[PDB]
Image (tube, coloured by chain):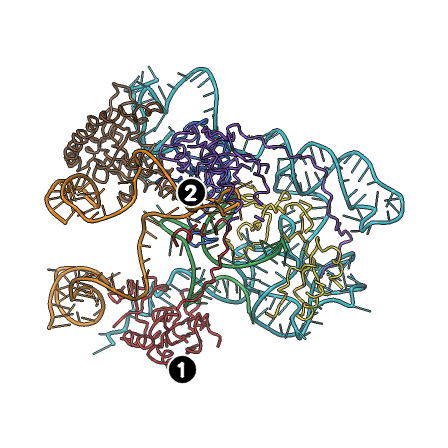
Chain colours: A blue, B red, C yellow, D brown, E purple, F orange, G cyan, H green
Amino acid sequence: AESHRLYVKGKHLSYQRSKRVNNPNVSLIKIEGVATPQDAQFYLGKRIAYVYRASKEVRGSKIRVMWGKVTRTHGNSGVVRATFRNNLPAKTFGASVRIFLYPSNI
Amino acid sequence: ARYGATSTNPAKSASARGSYLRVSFKNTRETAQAINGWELTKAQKYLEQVLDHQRAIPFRRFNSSIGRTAQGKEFGVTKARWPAKSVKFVQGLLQNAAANAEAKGLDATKLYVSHIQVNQAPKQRRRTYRAHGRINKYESSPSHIELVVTEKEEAVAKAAEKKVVRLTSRQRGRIAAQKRIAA
Amino acid sequence: ASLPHPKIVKKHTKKFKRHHSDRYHRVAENWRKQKGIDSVVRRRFRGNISQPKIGYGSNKKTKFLSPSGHKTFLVANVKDLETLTMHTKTYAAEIAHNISAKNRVVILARAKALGIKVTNPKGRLAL
Amino acid sequence: VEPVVVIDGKGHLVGRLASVVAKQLLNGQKIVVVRAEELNISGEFFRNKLKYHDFLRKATAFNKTRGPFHFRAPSRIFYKALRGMVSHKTARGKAALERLKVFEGIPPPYDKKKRVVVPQALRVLRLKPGRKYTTLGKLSTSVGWKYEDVVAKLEAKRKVSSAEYYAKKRAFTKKVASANATAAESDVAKQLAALGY
Amino acid sequence: SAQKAPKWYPSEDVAALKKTRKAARPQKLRASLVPGTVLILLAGRFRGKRVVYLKHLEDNTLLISGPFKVNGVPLRRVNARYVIATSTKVSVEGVNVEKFNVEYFAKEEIKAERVEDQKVVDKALIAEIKKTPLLKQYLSASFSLKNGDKPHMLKF
RNA sequence: UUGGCGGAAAGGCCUUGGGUGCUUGCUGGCGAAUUGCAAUGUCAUUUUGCGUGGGGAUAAAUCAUUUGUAUACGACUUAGA
RNA sequence: CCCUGAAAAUGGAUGGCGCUCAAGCGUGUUACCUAUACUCUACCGUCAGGGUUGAUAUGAUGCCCUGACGAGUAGGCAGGCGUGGAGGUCAGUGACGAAGCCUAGACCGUAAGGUCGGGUCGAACGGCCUCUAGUGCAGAUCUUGGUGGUAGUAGCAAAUA
RNA sequence: GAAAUUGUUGAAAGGGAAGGGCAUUUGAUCAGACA
């Protein structure tokens, strides 16, 4: 077909942060669609991957990845939390975000 | 000997120190930078045009509260002067080197200045009378001149890398599908 | 060629600079518990430097270990080398800077006849 | 939830429609408010013009320039109040403000193209009936916006060079209806509405 | 002796490990996975390739193949957690299965031992396949996440 | 390629007449494996540079000189095969 | 609750935008966010209690086990780090390059500081146990010497040329 | 033959300062580890 995608689309909103002090270790998820804490419960445990593109090729690719995962409901909305191996990079507040479907349970 | 940080083949090269020159340092800076990167033979024609308010030495760094001109305009600048004394030196060395290039047996239509630097050379103490019996200094900044005239050359070519490839077993057996399929 | 220790965690990898160092040319980066009554670094406020304190020590197990996991040891001459003989997995050597080149290769050589790793075999190599 | 997003201000509430579009934003949602001259606001027309009135005197003494610029132009306005809510003075800011355009009246690369609304920011569901309200339309005029009538002409237009897009999209879709019941009792169409559809 | 030398020189003994209490038990799978199921392989070379669950191995693995005649899907190990178990169900009455184990996949091109096992297994699948309808097709086509797709919903 | 529409930033939209593919509208037959149990598993669209090859064109400006409706100096305003 | 009463000087401040069956006021119900606080675990330290001479491996001021505590100016105590020289020691390093100096090269220590790679250089100098001191600097309108930005600037214009 | 402080060169950044903290990203640079 034309579609391949056997990830859910969705965005890097934040750091956890209080009004004036932020915590790069935790990140926040706008899963495109998911509006409640339930809807989020599905995507706990499911993996994430901010993909992006360096100029200088490594390692054989132009393309890099940081391996989430999703870990909990953040308050009302099924924003969710979202350690990653490496902390996402801020410039990323507003960047697209691959929730996957593995560590599956269906 | 022992010049600044050069970056060229000395076999096709000629150099020259004045030194302890009493011409002003902030002025000579400006003429030397203006000529830097030149085709030697043009450069001398450029400096002859200066003297001579025909065309100017564009002041870039040591240029504050200099006045402006239309001569510019040529260098994307408002502020520029005609510092004879600076030039006279700079073309007294350019003379020095094109004779220093001719006993090495370099082609005089190529040479070009590659590296030219001027420095604060040591001062020349003097003194002055200020109101109320105050003596100040009244120091002449002198200059250490030095240009490396060079035969210009072409391109390089490229050559490097050797871009060694360290990739995976998963990665091999994608590339494999690839030339098996198409190519 | 290690003794299967824990993980070598360091705590605070970054250098502890001295407050001001950047701003001054007079005030070294060498560390200085500030004594100022105004000081923002003393009153640790946010939002400045951390000051060095206990706290940051490093597990007793992995103290004084290269990453390899060996502790290094200063070896001026070959007698010197021959206390490490036994403890190759725990200790290591490092040849002193103030050795001639002819007396290095000797120590170098003496190293390997006994398994021992040195952490500066580069030294002063005529290469 | 898309790459772009064409809102039609009309029946809005600066104010509220206001946010949402700044929020969005900070979440990568290129947006493009149009029409606008037909914004809206709580409060009897008079005010607001009073309201307006100020953010006008506030100057800079010592050089009326270099000071707080009072735009007029519905657009700009919306803008502003949008803005105010997007921390500019940083980068993430800005990288925000770009994403957002804005015009009074649906020009081209949009008159095409569809548009939407923002319920939670519609007068008509916020307010209670009886409360007076505005119309950035007037407002802008009134504090001097040369161009409201040049829009209001290019409106008369495109409310047509539309309609007649329409009475043509609609005599189509209708035959498709009088040629869509011949084939459907078909076999394909009964299994279907068992799965649904 | 640049440096002196300690008194204490550690021991170089390496210890034994403490007697430990972690016995390996048998994986309890999620309940959807019954031999005779279509799966959907969520990753790998075959990401999205709808496939048929045949046997549970001991290494917890899933032995699956599509019907290689269908769809490119050979007999292959696959991990539970990279797989969506759906509803549909062939019967998997007639399949050998018992020859397949962890030693059969030992990275100790192709094998003809492995090629023959593909044909035998497939001929029993293909039969119970041609029972239902359009199923042969559903196995061929790759699964995907379209516009307005909501897994959470999407009851698999 | 026929013919039309559009200037609010048109830079797009519709339509005829052909040239030709693929057609999952229904039925088949080969191939896919070893990318070894997952690793984004790379198929977008930015701007620029260096040469082969198909059409086209064949200039100003600045300085210096000069004027004074101009002018602290730059700028301005004119003049000049 | 609104309103009048309600007048001060740059422009403007419920923090801002803005908000009107609120994003206002009063009250009630939940969910939710988040401090170096609380709970749990790791690591550091101090302090308290304990256990271990059997020779025979390495420290009995050692090796262990258990617990609770950790903010600090003035101030007190403690353990270290470094520098000049002195007794002892390693038959220590060294013209096959000591000291010094430069090094967005490495390693060690919480740190003071240590060690080493590379360059520069040319004659002496380190660990260790200990004695001893004219012993550690950012500040004193500190001293002495040097050098900046200021700046190619102020300006070099009285006495007819 | 140190620093201030200058001069080429090379790399980089810069919308009314600069510098510093935690955190990653990219660019340059390097240690060890593997046998």
Q: In which image quadrant can residue E20 be found?
A: top right
Q: Eyeballing the image, is C120 above or below C35?
A: below
Q: Position of residue C78 (x, y in %)?
A: 73, 65
Amino acid type for the residue under numbered disc 2: Thr
Circle 2 or circle 1, nearest the eye: 2
Report the disc number at residue C7: none
Q: Eyeballing the image, is C5 above or below C95?
A: above
Q: Which one is in front, G154 or C98?
A: C98
Report the disc number at residue A92: 2
* Viewport quadrant of the N terminus of chain E: bottom right
Write down the residue under mark 1.
B100
Q: Position of residue E86 (x, y in %)?
A: 46, 30
Callout 1 secondary element: loop
Could you classify mark 1 by the number of other residues whose Cα lies within 10 Å: few (under 14), some (14-19), or many (20 or more)? some
User: Residue drawn 41% across and 78% down?
Assistant: B12
Left or right: residue G88 compared with residue E107: right
Q: Which one is in front, D129 or E93?
A: E93
Amino acid type for the residue under numbered disc 1: Asn
